[PDB]
Length: 374
Ligand SMILES: O=C(Nc1ccc(F)cc1)C1(c2ccc(-c3nc4ccccc4[nH]3)cc2)COC1
Image 1 (cartoon, rainbow, N blue to C red):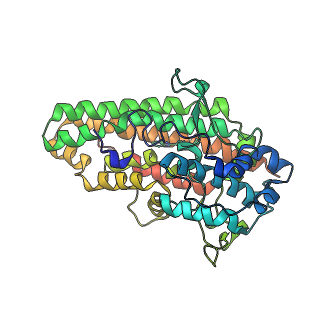
Image 2 (image 1 turned 60 degrees about the vertical axis):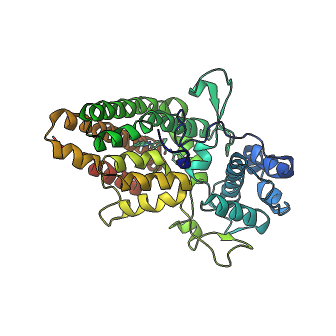
Image 3 (image 1 turned 180 degrees about the vertical axis):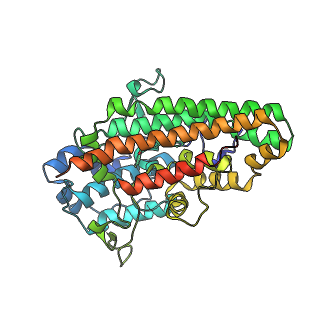
């Protein structure tokens, strides 16, 4: 079994298990804004409301789940504040009453002060009926940006794919134990189980089409997920008033921030972070946007011996076939992600009166393809 210091759940993997819905009474003003963002943004009172807030201390957020919920709340409020209605009217300064606690909370949890995958996917969910299981139909997001933004579809299908891949994560100890104990059959069985889980996760990914519209995603939700690293809209970055004097650059939300998105490439010796190129640079940089325990987990995978070298060293077709089943499943996940970017970003952008993500993902897939053994 995996160590508890890495904070990986048996059921939900890297996702935050049963995350908190309500902050303590001290932070009701935060929850008031975050709960009614679709109304407050559209009616144009979001920015005024945030500007009229008091600066609240973070010290009454005691346990982890409360601190994580606050990050989700504050993060969503920040993106709403920065982008507004999402028509290129941009706030270059985040006010100190929201900025100081958000940055202090961000420092405490070891994350950048900006909405990340961990917030808006891994912590942004609840069961409807606790007695019923984890499916889209028994689930809901805590927070959304606008009405008809498809944040439920986008975030929950991402979360279900995250949870699907969790079935493989618990096999990882078996993979490393088998190698040190030279248990070839156990290793073979283990790799096949990883491939089966990654095959299943692709099927779970298909739900994206059922619950997300292309035009809605591109025009509405994409803008709210955008950050301010290399963005012309905030050239110099955002100002966190009363915390840093100069503006600071931080990247927006990305599937690259998912620990699952990276960990299997690490496990299988696919050197995605090698090359010296933009893609490798990106994947490495996004480990800082993961929770500390998860970026430590990716580190300990890298520190363990190579599964690829072990398979190659044995002159074993079955082990190679099983290894390739995992590689093949990842290739299918990259290809499918590419189909999503085409449908949800490229085509809606052409209908406007994209590419860097395609090229990024094509490199990621190409590195995965070239790691096949047969
Ligand atoms: O962009 C996504 N989500 C997202 C992005 C930003 C954000 F702030 C919040 C959510 C989508 C997505 C893309 C790739 C994966 C994925 N999981 C993998 C596991 C293993 C290997 C390859 C994987 N790709 C999962 C979800 C959901 O529509 C595309």
